[PDB]
Image (cartoon, rainbow over all chains, first blue to last red; front, side, top):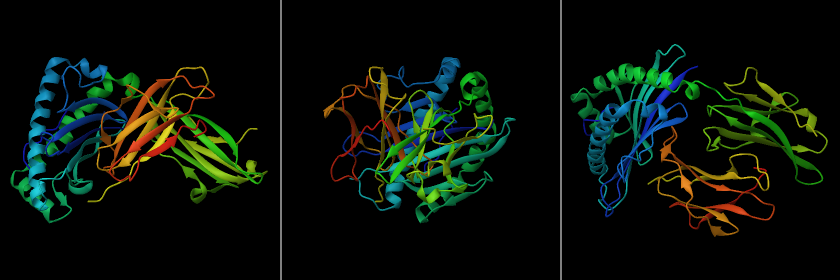
Length: 9
Length: 276
Length: 100
């Protein structure tokens, strides 16, 4: 199950 | 045995040739089970394990949407990192990440991982505490600031301790016949004359799964680390792996050499010799 | 920037036996950046429709790919893998040696 990447680096 | 789930993500800019390619590949141990690729011609193609297909369209639709969002986020992150390093818009750059969880035989969390590299260099990583970050440089300190402000570690912790562990357990159950089966190496020793004076002994391990293996030569019971040529473990294409280790030995001294093999699928470690 | 040149291994899926269908593999690993060109050759000529694995990498961040094609080894036919990468001034060729 993928993890959610939400916040730009 | 123990197991891991890990996603390997690569975002690659390509100025003049479209938006950055984004690919995310999921593994349980050494088995790839899903792949998402922004360059996929048809989503009907992005390969997935049989035991993932059984999760149905709801699982696939949810994961596809997460992937699409991840694509956007990493593309923006690529833009930001180019700025942090004062880089021109003309070059190609790479943002990679690895994340997931390691569990023991009981299925309990051993530790989680979430880390990132830029142009092949470590950039930022979530610490083992799943609460704090280690930034490699002043650029990554900016990312750390943004991620602390937005409480990203708390979200990643929830994923690593909850979602990751629960889904790994489910995949292990659905894929048990392969994922929980260790295939032992098939081993033998070959002999290859170099000159009148010496020959190579090569110790082979074939057909094993998972990839982790220890393959060593001893001479009179003493490890031959410096004198052993040891190739990287390599995939056969049928899920299994191969490796060999070789030593150069004086003619007539072959029986002083022993090959030693350790692997999860072996009830007992092996000791092998050349058998002419 | 810092680049890493590919390691190359060329080998068969199963132990080689003349006349018996098999798979010829070229495993490229340890490289960075990810763009790479790999060809399998038969007697010097490019083999068509070779397949490859999905881009992934090791925990040191270096990339790896497996290129593969079905083949039936013989005593006379020579096979090789030809690799090009930004780190290489010219293509690197590694011959298939059934003893390796």
